[PDB]
Image (tube, coloured by chain):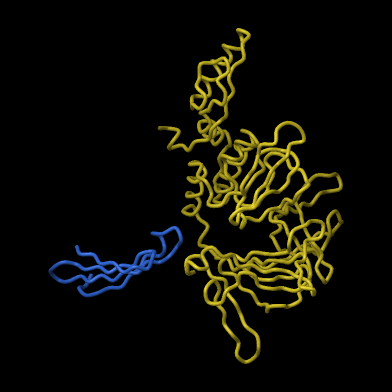
Amino acid sequence: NVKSVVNSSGKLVITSRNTELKLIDEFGRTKESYKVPYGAVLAKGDGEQVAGGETVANWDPHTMPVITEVSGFVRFTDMIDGQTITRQTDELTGLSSLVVLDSAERTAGGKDLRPALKIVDAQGNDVLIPGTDMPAQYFLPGKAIVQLEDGVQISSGDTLARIPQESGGTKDITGGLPRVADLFEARRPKEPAILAEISGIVSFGKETKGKRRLVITPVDGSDPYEEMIPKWRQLNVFEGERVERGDVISDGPEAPHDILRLRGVHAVTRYIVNEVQDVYRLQGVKINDKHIEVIVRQMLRKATIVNAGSSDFLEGEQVEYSRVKIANRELEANGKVGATYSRDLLGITKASL
Amino acid sequence: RSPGVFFDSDKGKTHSSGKVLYNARIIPYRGSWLDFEFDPKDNLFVRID
């Protein structure tokens, strides 16, 4: 899941959020695994042979940067003084420093605005990403620090701004139990990762009121899906390519319901088991996986009918999965055509009630 | 808590926008309390008991 680019010095900078590095022996057996953060610098390439004890990647763990993909001139778009950003001036020279505000301290005038950095050329037109047909612009979230001036020429792979991140507290059992309860209650994350609902080619369409549109054209069959992705959302897709079900249109934390709906039961059970075990394995607790698997089984007990079929179930009712299975296996023995359903995921509190 | 006037605020936990609301409370030794408060729309409001 590597998506990198070469900087001025000739090294390799990662532009992907889920890059995994692995060490493979000559037999082809993996032996070491690491995660590569966004904006990290790789000393070595992919597929090369290195010696034991050799540094391969470096990064700053305290700040998350934003790295440009195309060289050109930087300019501000929707950057309004004193209303959406706060600027300080180094009066000894012509330099200055800027901080992007958050939605907690901005007026209604800047409520609907969207500050960003735009990469243009010398001629003043918009520079597009090579290989695609989209403008080279980057949105700055709240509390970002920029060290550049308007019109400054920047090279590809250089950092345009830095985003500080908080430290945290102690990593003990009082800080993971909320995560375990979050997993077992199947809560929705604050901002999910948009996943492709159906497979096929992709293409964009109409744009309304600061909101994009995504139409996935299947290679054969219907063409129904018209997803209204928000404009502020960053996508990893472009018109013309093809995607499969469950692929990541936009990165972010996952939602267990989407995983269940798209990739199936085994995917969501594996995700839940791994996420829960990664909390206990930090504290030195050892627990088998049957115990979490039965809990996940108890969570997946409801099914919603999608077509009546030859059964007597209604169109949009929610019932027990076992009852649907019993009715369908009774109908299929008589030569009829049963009903079809969709599995549900419920929290333990809601499932028990 | 001693009698007098105290200025406090909520740490953005009352509004999903994370906007802090400030209030001033006058608490006497004997009588009725008084409260001045700010709303998310920046409108001063009064409150008794």
Which quadrant of the view contains residue A333? Answer: top right
Percent of width and height locating residue A264:
63, 34
Q: Nearer the viewer, residue A311 or A180?
A: A311
Percent of width and height locating residue A327:
54, 15
Q: Nearer the viewer, residue A253 or A80?
A: A80
Which quadrant of the view contains residue A44? Answer: bottom right
Residue that protrudes farthest toward the left in the picture? B30
Question: Who's yellow, chain-wise?
Answer: A
- Residue drawn at 79 percent across, 52 percent down: A23
Left/right placement of residue B17 relative to residue A18 reads left
Q: Nearer the viewer, residue A112 or A163?
A: A112
- Residue drawn at 72 percent across, 73 percent down: A74
Rendered-image quadrant of the C terminus of chain A:
top left
Residue that protrudes farthest toward the top in the picture? A334
Left/right placement of residue A352 relative to residue B33 reads right
What count of labels does the image hold?
0
> In the rendered image of this protein, does residue A34 appear above or below residue A200?
below
> In the rendered image of this protein, does residue A29 appear above or below residue A328?
below
- Residue drawn at 23 percent across, 65 percent down: B47
> In the rendered image of this protein, does residue A301 appear above or below residue B46?
above
Q: Say which colour chain B has.
A: blue
Q: Nearer the viewer, residue A236 or A28?
A: A236
Percent of width and height locating residue A60:
67, 68
Left/right placement of residue A14 relative to residue A89 reads right
Which quadrant of the view contains residue B3? Answer: bottom left
Percent of width and height locating residue B5:
24, 74
- Residue drawn at 81 percent across, 49 percent down: A24
